[PDB]
Amino acid sequence: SSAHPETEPKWWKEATFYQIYPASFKDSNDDGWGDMKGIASKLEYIKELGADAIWISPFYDSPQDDMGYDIANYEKVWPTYGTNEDCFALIEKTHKLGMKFITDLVINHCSSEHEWFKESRSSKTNPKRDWFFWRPPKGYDAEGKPIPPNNWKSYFGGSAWTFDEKTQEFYLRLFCSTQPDLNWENEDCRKAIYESAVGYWLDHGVDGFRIDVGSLYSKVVGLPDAPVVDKNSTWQSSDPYTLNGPRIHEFHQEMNQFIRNRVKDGREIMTVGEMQHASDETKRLYTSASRHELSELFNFSHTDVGTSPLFRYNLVPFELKDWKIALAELFRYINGTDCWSTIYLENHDQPRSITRFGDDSPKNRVISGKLLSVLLSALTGTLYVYQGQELGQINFKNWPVEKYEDVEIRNNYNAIKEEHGENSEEMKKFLEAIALISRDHARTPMQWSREEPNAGFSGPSAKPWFYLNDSFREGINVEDEIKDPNSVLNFWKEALKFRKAHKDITVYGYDFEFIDLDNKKLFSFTKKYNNKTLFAALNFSSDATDFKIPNDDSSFKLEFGNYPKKEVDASSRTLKPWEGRIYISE
Ligand SMILES: OC[C@H]1O[C@H](O)[C@H](O)[C@@H](O)[C@@H]1O
Ligand SMILES: [Ca+2]
Image (cartoon, rainbow, N blue to C red):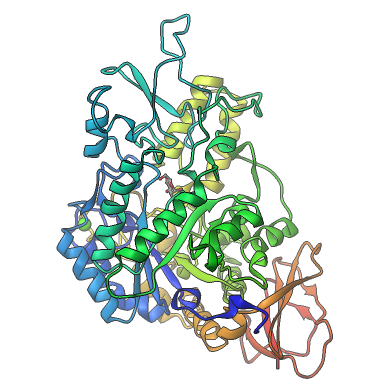
C-alpha cells in the first residue's frame, strides 16, 4: 500500500455522502416545498442510514428557473427554505451529529436577478459590464431578428445567447436564459465570486463544496463558432471552446489558494468538481493532491451510457461492458497516484439507477436494487448516495410531457418544436428518451410513508411543488421499508456497515482488474490491499450466470452479498438471478 499514495486516509475519502435535494426532501410547513427545518428533522434518519456527510443542492436565494442553480444571492438563503440562521443551525446540528456538511458552489453563472447582473445589464459603461459576456448581434436575419454572436447550443436546447433590448447586445448563457455566464477573465469578478460564494460559507463552517460545472469557467478567446458536428441541429456544442478551457487549471489553483488562506481553524476542506468529461490526464491535473486544485471529481461516462453523444435525449443501445468501462473511468486513473475518485450512480440530474442498470419490475426491483448496493459498496472512492436511492426508488411511468417540471425538458421540447416541428420524428425520439433519462426522475418528493396523497413529504392537505411518484403506494417509502427486514433500505444500511468495516480494501482498494470484461451479464473484478484480495461477482441479469475466482483457493471467504445469508452456498460458482457476492482473501 506504500506504492499507492492514494491509500493515505482522509475524512472525505472514506466518508459516505448523502445528497439532499432541498425542494424535494422534507416539507415542515405544508407549503409543498421542502425546507431546512424539514432537513433538520431528518438528520437522524441520515445518520442512521450510515452517512458520514451531507451535500445539499443549492438553497440560496433563486428564482428557481433552474431549481436553485440560478442564484440571485450567494449570501442569502432562499426565504422559502428558511433564514440564514436556520441554515447555520442546520450546519451546527449536522456537525453535532458527527457529520460533515458540503454546500453547492455554483459560480460558472449566476441568476440574471443577481445584483451583479442587474448592474452589468444596465448600460454598456458600468463597472460590471465585463463581469459577463456581452457581444453585439452578428447582424440581423431576413425577418429582422438579431443573429447571435456564434452558433453555440445551450445545455437545455436552442441558442446559448439571449438578446438584451436595452443595451442592444446578446449575453452568453450556456444554461437557461436567466443564467448568464460569469466572465472569469475579469479578475475583479473572480475575487468577488470568491468573497461571496466561497468565503461567506467558509466563515460559516462548511466542510467543503460540490463545484457545479467546474470545468466551464475558461472560455477560449473570441468565443468562436463551433464546428458543425450535428448536421440535424441549428446550434452546435460549444465543448471545444468551453469545456476544460486553457485557463481552467489556473482558475482552480487560484480558488484552492483562496480557500486555504480563508479557512480560520485549519480544518480540512473537500472540493468535489462536477467536471462532466475529462481525459485521464485532465483528471490527474484536477485531482492530484500535489496540484492543489480539486479533491475529486464527477465524470459522466457511466451515466451517459445508452444516450447519443450528439444529444442526451436520443437513446442508443448499450451492453454491460460499456457500463463497466464507463464506471471504471471514475477510479482506474488514480492507481498509484496522489489522486482521488468519486463513486455514484444517482444525483438530482439523473434517472433512477434500478431503472437504468437493474430491473425495476415488481419482481426484480428489490433484488436488483440490492445488487447495485453490493457493487457500490465495493468500489474505491468517495461514495455518494442520492435521496431515495436507499429506498430502491424507480423511474416514474407514463407521464405526459406536460407533467415534467424541468427547464431542461421544456427548453429542449420548444427547440425541437421550432426546428423540426411538434409532430416530427425528432420529437418522437425525444419523448421516448425523457421517459428513461429525465432529471425529473430524481426530483419527485422523498417518500417517507404510504400516507395519501403526499407520502409523508408534506401534510395531506398540501400541494407539493412537483408530483409524487406512484411508487410510494407500492411500499417504496421509509416507514414501510424500516419495518420490512428484507427492504432495500435495510440492505443499504448493511452495505454501508460492510464497506466501513472493510474500508482498507473497499474504499482504499487498488490494482482494480476486470474479470471477463466482455461478459454481457457478469460484472466481476478483483482489488488489492497489501496481502488482501477482494473479488466481486455480480450478475446483472435475470439468468443464472457462472463465474470463476482467479487463483481460487480456500482463503476466499464470502463477506457480503444480496441473497439470504443463510441460504447462499459460498462454494457455488453460479450466481442466481441478480445475485451479487463479495469475497475477501487475506
Ligand atoms: O447550473 C446548471 C447545471 O449545472 C449542473 O450540471 C447541475 O448539477 C444541474 O442541475 C444544473 O442544471
Ligand atoms: Ca416548506
